[PDB]
Length: 217
Ligand SMILES: [Ca+2]
Image (cartoon, rainbow, N blue to C red; front, side):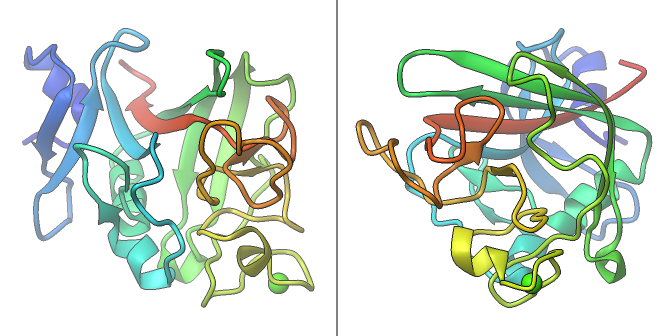
């Protein structure tokens, strides 16, 4: 029973696309995009953005259950992210592109997130890549927050200032779920789709993909 796109790959489907996966302890299947091209393939996409067609200003429940479509932009849903990352040890890669043709990535040796009663707190270790030398996600641990669930480390409400659902600190150095600003708009925006150690706190990115695979791939 395919638990993730790593399984899908090892069974010989080497072509990127929509696949269905059967996550342990989850009542129903789930479609995901599998990227089979990137490291040596194997990647379950957990979020993707590229055109702004999908709105990321959603509440806790939509963040939990997922929204959008794996043929385009989407958020896989926290409950599923937790569930997949409970099945084994996963690593996380984050593909990013700016408006001038540049591609960069961040990678994490180890990723998982807590369950809902842990506010889906992020845990990460082992940052490398070309999207900056420091990690733009906090490594040390942050809750997940959205407009209706204020779980950040700030006295202010970060999801309200920056939009979207994210592991905000006192809003920290990233928000890949902010507002999508188009070509030539990407400049001077404070609540865009940002990764501070790549392009900075006021650049809005052209495109993001967050994906996971097991260490033993
Ligand atoms: Ca707060």
